[PDB]
Length: 220
Image 1 (tube, rainbow, N blue to C red):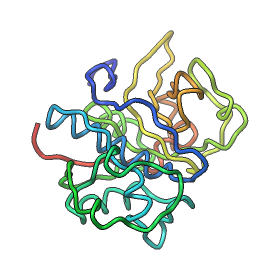
Image 2 (image 1 turned 180 degrees about the horizontal axis):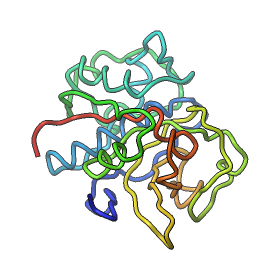
Image 3 (image 1 turned 90 degrees about the vertical axis):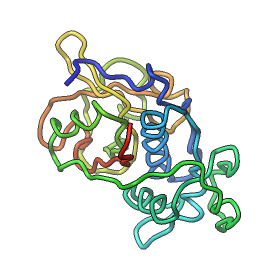
Image 4 (image 1 turned 135 degrees about the vertical axis):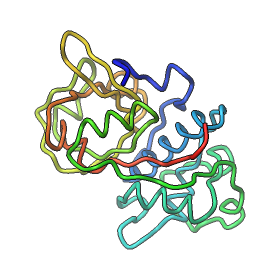
């Protein structure tokens, strides 16, 4: 595996978005991952619709602005046979009735999705070396909330209360990190991103290795 990976450097990451006052993070993480594999597979970067997932992807466990799961996100895109664009189905940070017309417009498709084996930073690194990966982590703590720069090494718990997207990894001064794309806008962290410690073992830093998944496209 490479020592450094950054999917932003090859145009596979859409500019930072902001989920606003809505617990839709699962949807932003789902979309960032799908956007990434689409560019990597097809060669074209397209910004995709979080709102569609919020409005049309409700399940028993996925509940619009009241939280949800990236696996349910991926399931929707597979089951629907695709996802519409950000421009066509814009984000309003509010739950709305599923727009059937816009649900029927499919600009990007995925073939499958896979879960990263739990508590396994090596399997996670393997996945990130090929594409962005959806993850959930413990983001509730003061220090995480007020992160502005550097490599985040905690403190944080391991509850998976907030979804983000790993868009790469690297090392500086012997300290390994993941590059994480958050959906709190450009004013949090390193213009919307965080470097968070990697190779700490177990569930990973803030539980980042607990619930990782990614969308699959068969051909490159």
